[PDB]
Image (tube, rainbow over all chains, first blue to last red; front, side, top):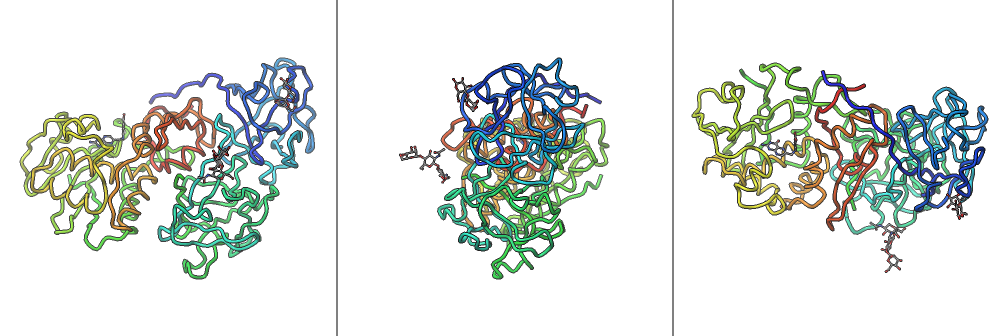
Length: 263
Length: 252
Ligand SMILES: *[C@@H]1O[C@H](CO)[C@@H](O[C@@H]2O[C@H](CO)[C@@H](O[C@@H]3O[C@H](CO)[C@@H](O)[C@H](O)[C@@H]3O)[C@H](O)[C@H]2NC(C)=O)[C@H](O)[C@H]1NC(C)=O
Ligand SMILES: Nc1nc(O)c2nc(CNc3ccc(C(=O)O)cc3)cnc2n1
Ligand SMILES: OC[C@H]1O[C@@H](O[C@H]2[C@H](O)[C@@H](O)[C@H](O)O[C@@H]2CO)[C@H](O)[C@@H](O)[C@H]1O
């Protein structure tokens, strides 16, 4: 065999709602200082170092969940005196920072600048969608699915179906937000929303509100699965003419496969 | 040994035929529960018998002339190829392959390792200008078939199959190529992720299963040539469309 290697501490940013970063209020390294959402940028309060022990901290003061219980906000405090469990965090590829011991996840009720974060009942919402990285800029990409066709965006509240790929039509230009949501590059105001949590449920392009329906996880298998409902987005009956993509039990078939291609 | 094999005839070949072909090749070399975030980790020398050390790729050109190249299950490498009672192995050529691949043909080893640089240097050109596609594939197989199998042709194959086998980005790049029946040349990105398979490999093995951030960063590149450093898996996938991981370290 050949055991891996214990990674050292690394500093990365944290985004998870309307392109806003997570940081310490007024950059005060003082204890008790709460954590809130705020426009990204070069500033320590925004930078967070991740350690092997499972901690995350800026300015040196560990990021702990302060009080503990669905609704308890987060803040920064000395690592030593920090409550053993209230300082350990988990960052699953599902784009969520869950707190081990508790089971609550860093939730952002609203995505308004200055909005304070807090541990809350994990329900799978865009609010509870975070992505740690130094590049707080989402990548533009076309969602090519069935028959090398690109997923097309229509009108607000309107459906979304497969249309002949066109690297020029902005209606096919999708911006993958760090909050684990998919919004129109043209207008990042509307996220790819679903109409229900049952199979055959129609998908559309509703507004962005952090709803559990606007939370999309890109499975490494090539399927864009809805987190709340294990259903995946697919080409209804395969008949692209029907003009409708919906949520449906993962079958492992091509009509459920999607490829995210650059610009 | 009668190593398993997958085929792909350019003639009457649709984008889907290619996509399916690649899948099969993956289901082959990619086995063994060891896998992170859903992506498998190609076995290592110790955990792979000679009876399953190689997989053959039967590629049929338009004119029907089909050439076959064996891939190394432990890395998806183009170990060698054979054309009508003829077999060729790179300057390297281990006794394992030299004594188990295309037994019966003429075993004349080429004069340059499979290393990308080695090929580009032998082909007199760099990947950045060896256009791949439906037609380029035909000429490739053809050149390997008749001309004996030069570097350039091999370089055209390596990316069209192994590369596309581990990178779905390259997959679709080819899929659209056959779809529109038009060629294309590797861009800064495709070429970058092409050189960062090992790096991004361990970077993902480091973080581990269900872990998003990377202990380090992957040095990819945009078309303009500017550096595109991905620090998380989600990014690496949504861009490189990676589907095959290379072993470097074992979980911890
Ligand atoms: C996706 O949509 C977003 C907008 O929702 C685009 O963002 C920004 O787009 C502008 C225009 O191309 C980029 O440059 C701008 O140029 C104008 C004209 O010189 C200038 O007045 C602006 O100050 C800015 O330099 C800008 O770089 C780009 N990104 C950002 C972060 O601002 C984006 O370009 C769209 N992406 C694609 C692939 O269409
Ligand atoms: N003959 C041959 N056959 C390949 O399949 C291949 N793939 C790549 C591109 N991908 C890799 C793969 C592995 C490694 C590493 O272990 O270091 C580096 C780059 C480059 N040359 C290659 N040459
Ligand atoms: O609280 C919101 C947001 O504001 C900034 O905080 C301070 C910053 O730490 C300080 O160095 C500067 O002089 O004044 C800012 C006032 O807003 C930070 O940019 C950010 O991280 C948050 O702290």
